[PDB]
Image 1 (cartoon, each protein chain N blue to C red):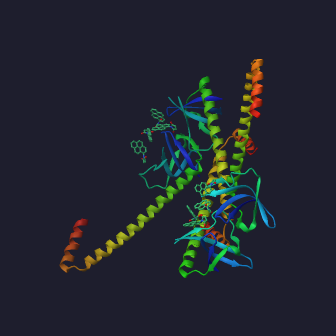
Image 2 (image 1 turned 90 degrees about the vertical axis):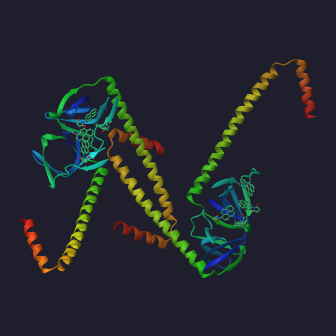
Image 3 (image 1 turned 45 degrees about the horizontal axis):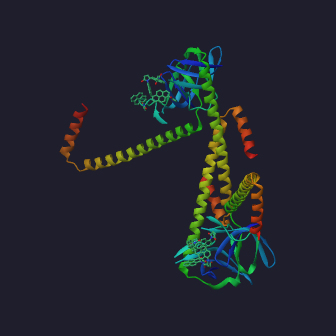
Length: 123
Length: 123
Length: 123
Length: 123
Ligand SMILES: *C1=CC(=O)N(c2ccc3ccc4cccc5ccc2c3c45)C1=O
Ligand SMILES: *C1=CC(=O)N(c2ccc3ccc4cccc5ccc2c3c45)C1=O
Ligand SMILES: *C1=CC(=O)N(c2ccc3ccc4cccc5ccc2c3c45)C1=O
Ligand SMILES: *C1=CC(=O)N(c2ccc3ccc4cccc5ccc2c3c45)C1=O
Ligand SMILES: *C1=CC(=O)N(c2ccc3ccc4cccc5ccc2c3c45)C1=O
Ligand SMILES: *C1=CC(=O)N(c2ccc3ccc4cccc5ccc2c3c45)C1=O
Ligand SMILES: *C1=CC(=O)N(c2ccc3ccc4cccc5ccc2c3c45)C1=O
Ligand SMILES: *C1=CC(=O)N(c2ccc3ccc4cccc5ccc2c3c45)C1=O
């Protein structure tokens, strides 16, 4: 149910909406800058945002081109996210392996000092 | 038993030595460059190195200043190693936490695609 | 309950909120300038601010990084406040001591004139 | 059994070694230039080189990074060799085909003269 929302604060946002008796929920909202798509709330990790219907100006069905652009944007963002996750996987694996290798070639007294220092760190 | 070793290849190396009937073992060897101390074998992680006595020119007891410098050098190296280990601990902890936070705010389909992609990676 | 508030006047403010049936209270509110945190009401000394729910656009849970930055900002502000209080303590103590020392080395007639002048001041 | 060998001629060479009672064999030896890996004996086609143990200074186990670099170097060299073999296969096939085509369009007297000339060549 991809639709365009007009907010009271002269804002146009496209997203997948679900309508209830008094309030509506929106997913993957994007503000439209005359086109440029920008994340509506780049401060939260919530999947959906609830909003009262009293702050609604117009609800409408967008054009096919807008829907296609919205789909492409979301797909590109998700692909970037999964690529970043894979990159972080590889980086953390490499770092852990090299750190373990460094830890292996240590001295008993140095190991005890490291343990005490880490205990003081966590203190 | 900190002592100075003269090798057949015109080399002077100071280290803690243990003498056996045919071969001798050395720990924390350091070549002396006319003074500059350099690691003797910066390619292995072994704690001690065994060497036949037939390749021995002279064994001798060093001066007090040389022993003090050797002790200071070893202590500084060990302190640097433990500091690096602590730094790596902090870095890997931060990276793992941020990666988990990134993983939390994902989509089910994206998570499935990530799982399949990781399986293909390990393939 | 650190949360992000969207006001009707296109404003985003993070703070510790408490929700009631008709109105909500907020503590340590901070406007977000695209990040920069600014005090929401730098004109009042009240600990909490009450606001009707009819002026609410969205309530949401922020990210971990935002919460950490908010905590650090509040802690830094409180530390600055307590340091300023200590500085003022020291300054007023020094000023009072030096003023008392000045008052000690006076003349009886001058003291009477000072008393009359202070009485006229308060008149 | 990838290990580092110190020779009497102030040389460090890494390779896969096999130890016997009096002599040791080494495969894929590589001199280390402070890192740069160079073929130890770029004059022979022998798979393994035998050497007496009396010319041994130190035998040691290298680090994981050195082993990884050695493996990568050997794999790259083998891939280059097989690629060159394939290139030579293609070149010799093309040359033989074109030479046969040239031989086909000849004259009987010219063919006899060619046969006599080749016989004189081999003489
Ligand atoms: C109320 C305050 C404010 O800043 N608003 C606002 C929010 C978003 C936009 C986006 C684009 C745009 C272009 C020209 C003017 C203009 C004015 C105000 C806003 C704008 C905006 C509010 O709605
Ligand atoms: C994210 C993308 C975007 O365009 N944003 C945005 C939305 C509304 C406004 C209103 C006013 C204004 C003034 C100066 C700069 C600026 C930047 C971005 C936005 C602005 C904006 C996003 O928040
Ligand atoms: C045999 C070969 C070689 O290179 N050697 C060698 C090893 C270490 C050193 C250290 C310092 C130094 C100073 C001046 C000359 C010189 C020559 C050779 C070596 C030197 C070296 C061997 O012993
Ligand atoms: C590590 C420290 C050091 O001084 N090394 C060293 C030992 C022997 C030699 C011999 C010859 C030579 C020629 C050019 C450069 C160079 C650098 C370091 C050394 C050299 C050396 C160590 O291996
Ligand atoms: C209404 C009047 C006004 O001035 N508003 C306002 C309040 C705060 C901000 C903060 C940042 C910002 C950036 C770009 C444009 C813009 C417009 C209006 C405001 C802004 C603002 C009102 O909301
Ligand atoms: C305190 C910090 C801050 O950024 N404030 C702030 C909030 C809203 C606005 C809106 C418009 C405007 C125009 C010119 C200057 C200016 C300065 C600060 C603010 C402004 C603002 C605070 O009040
Ligand atoms: C004996 C003669 C000779 O030339 N040696 C020799 C063999 C290999 C190397 C490699 C690198 C290097 C660096 C600095 C000095 C130096 C000296 C001698 C050799 C060196 C070498 C012998 O060992
Ligand atoms: C192959 C690679 C390499 O580095 N080689 C090599 C080994 C030892 C020496 C010793 C002395 C010397 C003097 C001038 C040039 C030169 C080049 C290469 C080597 C040298 C060397 C190989 O043989």
